[PDB]
Image (cartoon, rainbow, N blue to C red; front, side, top):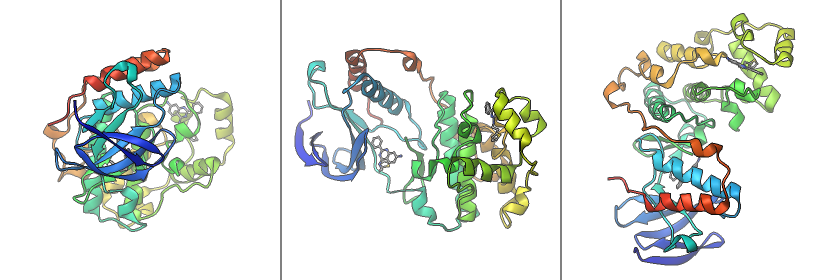
Length: 333
Ligand SMILES: Nc1ccc2c(NCCc3cccs3)nc(-c3ccccc3)nc2c1
Ligand SMILES: Nc1ccc2c(NCCc3cccs3)nc(-c3ccccc3)nc2c1
């Protein structure tokens, strides 16, 4: 129904509704390539992502369905969402390309830090938005698992969105391949991010996988008696006992000059035991965010049906389910 036009971008033929003008490449990768554009219907600058080989295999097809289901479900100011999704195909039989459209963001978190301290007012506002979006994501029973400055976009008014080395911000239970980690692995990442904003430097800049765990234990101490009781691995538990004990450090002496409320929040985020970590909802009520907290405007998500993750289907079945989601899409107001 919309009039499409073809154009040569990256190494391939983009077919795109005429409402999107001035297509200009921004990136590339195994799973897709992205162009910046201008949406003449809305007047917004947008990013258009063309999925790469979306139905080449069963794995690609399930990936394409997962990515579209996820981005269609996210409707929150501090999480990336869909402005549009389209295909040049007029029927399922000729359905072979998928394009996703989102609001163009000018920079990520690295771009605003630049190895410099942010003010406490600024960190308050940025971490509040991350936690606000995290509360929404976690309420849908989703775990992000890869929170880091490059996965956090910010515009010129400092409005932040969570996007779709990484080990610097990874929770220690992931580093040790524990099977049953919970949502507070993301809270660990936010603690690492917040520390970096206040100090201007990476909190745990490990040079490899084992060095990363070494730096973490030097700050938060060796596992306590109560945490060792919950470790099922006999090899892990034995190795931990053989280590020289290290005292949990006093964050107030580590982050000198910081807001004491900021230090108290970091203490509650960077706990080794993930069962004792503050949740996103609890962190929003912390006194550190007094000037931004509003419990009437920190919404949760609708329930998100993730049962498809357990399913093994054929290429054409994932493709047809993906086609259903393209057709049923409703643009936001
Ligand atoms: N971790 C990242 C990093 C970059 C990203 C990026 N391109 C950078 C320019 C941006 C456009 C919109 C938000 S950010 N774009 C998209 C994306 C674009 C369109 C549809 C779905 C996703 N995700 C990103 C995830
Ligand atoms: N209820 C909990 C809470 C936390 C846990 C945790 N956290 C990581 C603790 C350490 C991280 C680095 C050195 S010790 N790690 C493991 C675990 C680690 C290795 C093999 C099997 C399980 N279980 C946990 C269960």
